[PDB]
Image (cartoon, rainbow, N blue to C red; front, side, top):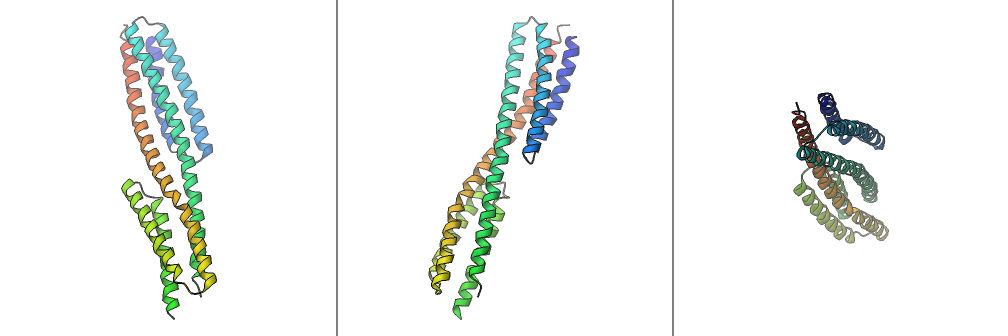
Length: 229
């Protein structure tokens, strides 16, 4: 009976722990909402069995430990929900910005298409490809010092690039390249969104680790309550 409630709490714990992995592997809003709907139904059932279990209890010290184990699980799960949703918007903000940056880069490299104007247009062409490779590499990095180094490296390339387009002779080419570079330079805010996505991923991993420890502490208090036999 206290044993009947404890077995259900222990099995809903392991289910919630899988729904949390489902939630953190969600790739879009539909999946994120569907994993969140399942996790809330399972937490609601877990809470009715916890309530049955304590209704039949007297040890107020145990009951205080159980109430604080339950509040910790509920806060840990509400915080991971905010984190996971912030993870999908941040990934979006970054991909939209990388795609605007890829279009401006291609357009810049096409203005360089046609004696020493030639090797000069070819160097600008190579530099626009290397800044686009930097941005494609930067959104795949999981190390934070590397993210910051690519950021200052892309910024120094952008400076070299704008000083090379001043040496460009055709007046019109010169200015169409120069305004693309100033559009590209405005999108450099994507590297501070890459740093927020790193910090949010790290906070979310720490939170999932805390979920396993919190659930292990919750069942360890309910097993103590069932030595009421």
